[PDB]
Amino acid sequence: LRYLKRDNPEKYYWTIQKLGLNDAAITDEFNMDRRYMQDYEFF
Amino acid sequence: EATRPLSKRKFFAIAEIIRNKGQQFALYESEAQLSVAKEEAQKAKEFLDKRSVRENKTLLRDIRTIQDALTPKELLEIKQRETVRQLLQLDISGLEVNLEK
Amino acid sequence: MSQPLLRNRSPEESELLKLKRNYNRSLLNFQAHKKKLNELLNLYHVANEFIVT
Amino acid sequence: MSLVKLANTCAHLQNCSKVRVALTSIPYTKLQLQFAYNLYQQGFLSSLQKGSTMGPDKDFVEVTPDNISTRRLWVGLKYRDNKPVLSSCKLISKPNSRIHLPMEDMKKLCSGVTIRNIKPLQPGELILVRAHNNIMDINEAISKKLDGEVLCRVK
Amino acid sequence: TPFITRIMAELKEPLVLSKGYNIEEVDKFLAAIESAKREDIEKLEDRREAILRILS
Amino acid sequence: ATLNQIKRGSGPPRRKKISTAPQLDQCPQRKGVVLRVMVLKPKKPNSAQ
Amino acid sequence: MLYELIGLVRITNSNAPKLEAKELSSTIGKLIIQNRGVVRDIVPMGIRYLPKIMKKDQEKHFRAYHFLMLFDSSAAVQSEILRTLKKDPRVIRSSIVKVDLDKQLDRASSLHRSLGKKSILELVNEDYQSI
RNA sequence: CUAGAGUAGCGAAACGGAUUCGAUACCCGUGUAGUUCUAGUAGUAAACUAUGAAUACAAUUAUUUAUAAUAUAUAUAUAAAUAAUAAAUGAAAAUGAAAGUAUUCCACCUGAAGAGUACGUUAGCAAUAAUGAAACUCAAAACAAUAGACGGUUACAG
RNA sequence: UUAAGAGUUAAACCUAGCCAACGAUCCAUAAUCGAUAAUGAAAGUUAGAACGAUCACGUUGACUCUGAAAUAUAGUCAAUA
RNA sequence: UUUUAUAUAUAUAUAAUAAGGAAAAGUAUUUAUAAGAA
Ligand SMILES: [Mg+2]
Ligand SMILES: [Mg+2]
Ligand SMILES: [Mg+2]
Ligand SMILES: [Mg+2]
Ligand SMILES: [Mg+2]
Ligand SMILES: [Mg+2]
Ligand SMILES: [Mg+2]
Ligand SMILES: [Mg+2]
Ligand SMILES: [Mg+2]
Ligand SMILES: [Mg+2]
Ligand SMILES: [Mg+2]
Ligand SMILES: [Mg+2]
Ligand SMILES: [Mg+2]
Ligand SMILES: [Mg+2]
Ligand SMILES: [Mg+2]
Ligand SMILES: [Mg+2]
Ligand SMILES: [Mg+2]
Ligand SMILES: [Mg+2]
Ligand SMILES: [Mg+2]
Ligand SMILES: [Mg+2]
Ligand SMILES: [Mg+2]
Ligand SMILES: [Mg+2]
Ligand SMILES: [Mg+2]
Ligand SMILES: [Mg+2]
Ligand SMILES: [Mg+2]
């Protein structure tokens, strides 16, 4: 999705909106650390 | 570009924007939101319609009744609901003719 | 050394190539679906032995 | 223009010289073709040929995007007096450190003076320079008064 | 998110068949086979139900 | 050994000549007062007073 | 999913060994069909002495009526069938194994497949099966 | 290590029996924690291939291993694993498709000992884990291989 | 207010920002440099005595007049002697 | 190779045929410079 942003920004925003995600969720560094699983209540 | 001191730490001012990628990234965002809403609504309408069709919902028995006929009233009702060939024409034939084309 | 390395594909050549590729895709899809229909027919031929009642 | 690919080609030619194969294949690109032509003009390579991944072209084949992936440039190596003519092939300007020299520094390098830790040109050696997407020997680039990127050494 | 919910719903609808089969297509194919053979109704319905259960 | 590792501070150790007479504070010599005169025994294989 | 069940039913009545296997087959088949299942085949293996004097609950068994059931069904009711089998005193031993249907929709049991008959269509032979 | 349950065998510690100049050890008996399960803390091993990852190339043989064919036979072709090698490299042992020819990135090292020690800081319920010196002493210290001696080192003969 | 910009200083009202593991903030140390000196094949490394350029200081700290320019080796006040 | 022939259904299988030969005498400055030993 970051490549899609670098290539076709309009389709990038369309796709992330359709999939239920935002720009921050794609661009920001992400690890499935215990902090994420606690904050978002994965379990 | 260089400028008089405008604050403690600010000594430069923008002069022009060669690439408007940052500007476009918000216009496209809003447009994507607006378009996704309407496309969602349309596809949800289609799904609800299909649910209604499946709610409304015997082809073998019906076709056999037409075949044996070749009684009159039920036959007419089934007609409203080579005719056997038309009612059983399969999408695979369309694929075959398209491939040949 | 100072001339183009390759000859660019014309739009007409690209159209013909795309038509060939689409035909290949649709052909493979067709054999897949027809094989699936054949398996369905073979299963129908033996559905009588299967107990559902 | 990948300097990585030129390094790979240099190592490939060195390996081929060690095992003494009479023919070898390298990627078919403008930079590689110009580099091979420059080596051939100096006499380091016996022959240039255009071909596929399997071998030289039996008949002339036009180069198009359809077959570009499978195109190769086949070079014939020379072994004279029980010694390889093309013995060592190295890079001066590496991808991590790229060296662009002005003309006067290029003359100084040819004249025995070490410039930016590059060993000076040796008598029977050839140094290749790239200027305006054209590959030439250092002497020509000096005669053309062109500032350029100093790529490789062939001794 | 509308898209994931729609896809999950369509998966969870009744009379959804696996292995790339479509219920209407299967019914039409079975009727075509019966017509071709013609050219016991509870037993034909039993074959249909067994096929649907297997492919459900 | 990599270029970026040399950039960050990697390189040959300095041939730094450590001072063998630190207490003089980089002076050719210093005046002093004798606290005691001591007679030591040298390390073997040397022997003397 | 196609599941092959191999049950080892106990023989208590020396005069009619098949009765208990009949009752068990009826129960399992009824469960499978009433929970949206299909019973493709029931292969009646014979009476065989068990390899050892196997023990279920307090009774000790030396022989058993072996039987096989090939049935297409879902995972949940398959686990339910297994649970009913394990607690039933009649079933000395039970085992359910998946028969994969990724390539061919119709497959025979392990016994017929080992004999050489890959499918049940081959089992019932092929005449006027090209319709 | 922290809570619960479990505890058949094994078994730190402990209690005794032997051996011994002495036994604080090896051997023997009873055996606590632990080994086990669940819910956690911690994040160290000779955590080793003592060999970071990716890419291009590099001469053979033999087996397998996995595919693709062609009619068991083509000692069939394409790949990877394994073994021995050529060149190459190396202080050598040796590596051998990497310890070779090249490119890119990261981590690490700068004599032995003091020392992974002290102090401080961070985290953990704690044991501890991470980070991590300096003074002083010395001309040492280590790796591979060579020839010897030696072994409560093997086998073969006389 | 200045001849002059600016949180430089003084006042007012808003925004939540700014720097930082490519090392902030804090601490220790240090006058800086050259077509100057030493050394090296050179890149560099060391010095900053002597020649030359810049800065700061004239026992310590703050402020004031004059002035174009001074917190002046001035004046006032205090500290030290 | 190329071209053509016969035969067979624009193409395929067989057979023949190949244009690349030119000669002549005479016409320095090179650079900067890295040594180890017990
Ligand atoms: Mg401002
Ligand atoms: Mg416990
Ligand atoms: Mg225990
Ligand atoms: Mg014990
Ligand atoms: Mg001992
Ligand atoms: Mg003991
Ligand atoms: Mg434990
Ligand atoms: Mg943990
Ligand atoms: Mg430890
Ligand atoms: Mg460690
Ligand atoms: Mg290690
Ligand atoms: Mg080594
Ligand atoms: Mg520690
Ligand atoms: Mg202002
Ligand atoms: Mg301020
Ligand atoms: Mg204010
Ligand atoms: Mg700092
Ligand atoms: Mg000072
Ligand atoms: Mg000073
Ligand atoms: Mg001076
Ligand atoms: Mg200094
Ligand atoms: Mg002086
Ligand atoms: Mg002053
Ligand atoms: Mg003063
Ligand atoms: Mg004084």
Image (cartoon, coloured by chain):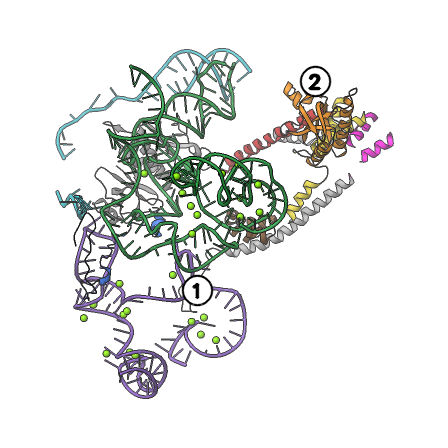
Chain colours: A brown, C red, E yellow, F blue, G orange, H green, I purple, J cyan
Query: Which residue is at 24% across, 38% downward?
Result: D125
Above/below status of A25 relative to I66: above
Q: Is residue B2 magenta?
A: no
Quadrant showing the C terminus of chain B: top right
Chain of the residue under label 2: G
Q: Pick the residue in front: D84 or F47.
A: F47
Q: Is residue B20 left or right of residue I23?
A: right
Disc 1 to disc 2: CB gap under 8 Å: no
Q: Is residue G66 left or right of residue B65?
A: left
Q: Is mark 2 within 8 Å of ligand 8?
A: no
Residue type indicated by callout 1:
Ala
Residue that badge 1 annotates: B13
Looking at the rendered structure, the secondary structure element under dot 2 is loop
Q: Is residue B74 magenta?
A: yes
Quadrant showing the N terminus of chain B: bottom left
Q: Which residues are the magenta region?
A: B57-82
Residue G125's disc is: 2
Q: Is residue B70 visible?
A: no
Which one is in front in this view, the residue at disc 1 or the one at disc 2?
A: 2
Q: Pick the residue in front: A36 or D152.
A: A36
Tag count? 2
Query: Which residue is at 22% across, 40% downward?
Result: D122
Residue G79's disc is: none
Please state the horizontal and vertical placement of residue C44, each as a whole percent of the image.
72, 26
Please state the horizontal and vertical placement of residue I56, each as a whole percent of the image.
29, 74
